[PDB]
Length: 310
Image 1 (tube, rainbow, N blue to C red):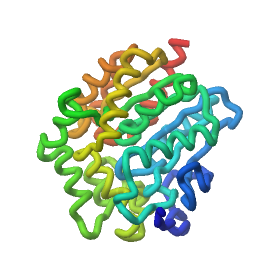
Image 2: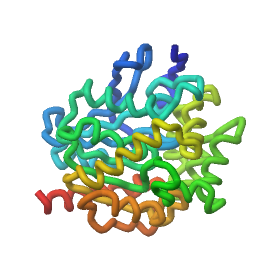
Image 3: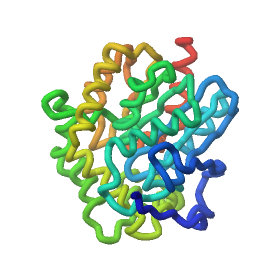
Image 4: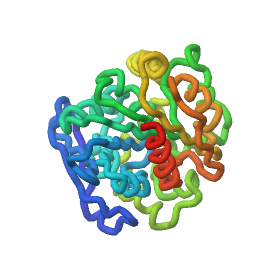
């Protein structure tokens, strides 16, 4: 029952621009023996809380440029590392990672920390999973900041959320290929390719959580879950659509990384239509899949947009 390993702390000693202190939650309901890492920045008694969820194959380090902007506005910021990523523990078997394994973890984190007045900030898997959280506990969610992401429903229901899987060849097909094929996966090399504006140091931070391949079962399972969606993922994702379309009435802000070959306009415009009240998206011409690397701007504009609608 959940064989996992922990990344030696020395691997995080020379992180670039990541002065955020570690917080851990051991033995969350349904996660015995697993220690989860998360950042808790800004006023801990703040009324507003920004839940920042990362994706594949990154960690909370991805939100490092957005965190300060949010904390400065007077809000609290929670940025958790999924099991298998960042400083959280990493199950050694790919079988242990599932849509509900990661989803239930997010729900347990929300209940444990008793988060309220939440502004959900998502991208990629943070969105696939994150966008399904509100419907399970609506009163806790207030706003949404969505960057390149969608819902993992079936091809018939939403063809746009499946089409990108097979085309273009240099889009998700290439992304997935780079992650599931190399016997010796080097995430610093991966991130420099998929986020060409990263410095050598920043790229090193993405490799930091993984001393060797045995620490990458979670990294290898995520892309596979996008291509092969189980029934639970499909149903949860389909129920999520109805929520964003008929139940959601909170403030929303969308930003599109225009150079994203995976989840750009093809996926983001159909998403905008599904989220009730979603305004015209902020198009970021230079941004890639990892919109957060251009996050200071997204952070500032999201706060400005939220204030004008208070």
